[PDB]
Amino acid sequence: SARKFADEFREMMKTGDSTKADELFDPNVRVEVGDKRYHGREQAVDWIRHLVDRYDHIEIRIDHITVRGDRISIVFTVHYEKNGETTYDRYVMVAVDRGRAQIKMLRKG
């Protein structure tokens, strides 16, 4: 289940699909990207779509998936390529399984 969830999240991150986001994001999801803070599905989707529009390629690698009780923690790195320069970010994501896992927090870390 946790791996399926991570795979779906990676696929959603390619296109910023709103339908997928409705399934994967908690309605009150918090996304922290350095100084910028997003709240809710719509802002989380817009954040993803801005990335998709800006970079030549985005590679997402799921590094760690850990489950403790109903808590799913995923550490992933994102490689953003733009005009021969690549930026290497790392994110930590907390999702809660309630049968149905939903992302509560996504933070650049």
Image: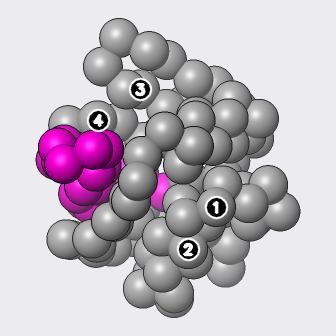
- Label 2: element kind: helix
Amino acid type, label 1: Thr
Cβ–Cβ under 8 Å for marks 3 and 1: no
Q: Main secondary structure of the magenta part?
A: strand
Cβ–Cβ under 8 Å for marks 4 and 2: no
Amino acid type, label 2: Glu
* Residue visible at 57% across and 43% down in the picture: 53
Cβ–Cβ under 8 Å for marks 2 and 3: no
Tell me, yes or no, whether the highlighted magenta stretch contains residue 93: yes
Disc 3 target residue: 32
Query: Disc 2 and disc 1: Cα gap in Å?
Result: 7 Å
Disc 1 target residue: 15
Which comes before the other along the chain, label 4 or label 2? 2
Disc 2 target residue: 11
Amino acid type, label 4: Lys
Cβ–Cβ under 8 Å for marks 2 and 1: yes
Q: Which mark is residue 108?
A: 4
* Camera sees residue 9: no
Query: Disc 2 and disc 3: Cα gap in Å?
Result: 20 Å
Quarter of the picture containing the C terminus is: top left
Q: Which residues are magenta?
A: 74-96
Label 4 packing within 10 angstroms: few (<14), some (14-19), many (20+): some
In x, y percent, where is residue 3?
42, 85
| Viewer-side residue, 79 vs 38 | 79
